[PDB]
Length: 224
Image (cartoon, rainbow, N blue to C red):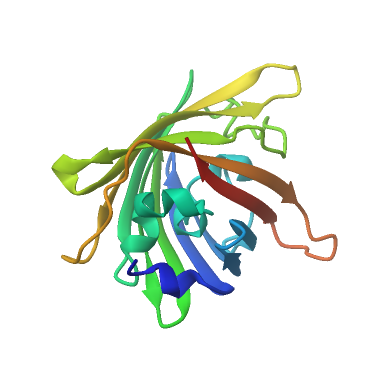
């Protein structure tokens, strides 16, 4: 089980995101640690360019599934850890219903003992007065699952899932995700049988942090 050993204890994480939505540029940096044994992620993200032009909840999925807890009987289906330390490229298109879309390209890999997630995000066709640019989304999270399937044609995995972002009027802003992950090394990786990753999220704020930011606590477990 190559790559698994790199996740046996607590691992420091660094996230770097460069975005541009409807021409509005922004950057986000994140730091924290992951404990894959418990499928636990603890991270704090900061918008280093000022005010985030989009809702923090809409960036959660974009901002390291290698930290998921895979039950012992499912260890042969952990594509994410198997690609380490070289890593994998993670790409998505996220369609916000009745609004614009995000296109993301990220590289997740180890740089020394730090697991790094470096992201490029481009958003187009958003409504200036819509739920995203207008910041009309509640600061929380309710979606949990994603069905992961193998993508042999690309020697990786893929997934399609909907994320629901609660709005104050009781309605929901849908964010339809289409995902594809491919290894960075020419090395071996595990192409998994179908399964789910179920994530419990928790968004919060550091009462003593003045910069625009997001504190995130997540627990992810594989099943199915």
